[PDB]
Amino acid sequence: GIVEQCCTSICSLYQLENYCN
Amino acid sequence: FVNQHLCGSHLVEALYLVCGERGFYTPKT
Image (cartoon, rainbow over the protein chains, first blue to last red):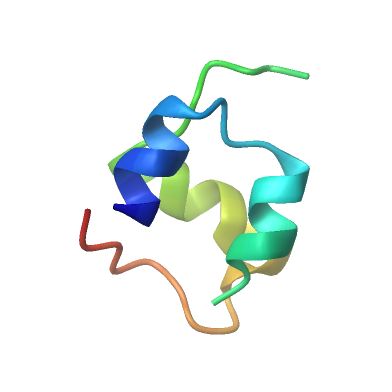
């Protein structure tokens, strides 16, 4: 989930913003 | 952007820094 999600959906700013935990 | 995706070490480093050394570094897939 969420982690592989960053490892594959280009994980950038918006990610961080929506990831901040 | 650098858009090379982020996993384990990089992933954690990455957000940690931008908005992660608030909860972060233990990302269970």
